[PDB]
Length: 195
Image (cartoon, rainbow, N blue to C red):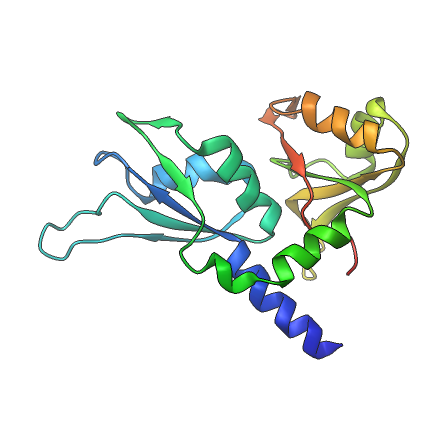
């Protein structure tokens, strides 16, 4: 129960991290932050560092808050030209340690027609997002993630559609949709609303 919750949180910590390789030498942490922030709020960045060269070693780890952001970054940023080099975005070497929970979460997610939306402007609320996305079909829920303190939303959320066709169409259609001067990033959920 609470034990299952701890096991899931450990798996999720692993699942929220991506390896970013082939980082061009001109890039540093702020550029990596801006390149990977569209997919979800970044919880931390760990740049590689050489103490003798005083420079990074071409790679970094980006840590998100939900695994959908890491999945989306893997999908959308692998082989993107950052600076003068196409980057590699991959799983962390310990991703296998999220088994079996990683698969269990996906199987639970298959029961729902749920999508993940990031780069949601801080001035929008859940009903604003619902209105835009119900173009693709009836929505059962549209929830922006909120910080307990302040109650402000974190720039991302999840939408559950009644029909799989609708969630598929939203994911196929809405990437880079301009909402409030931010360009939405949209992907499938890999976790259920509730396990």
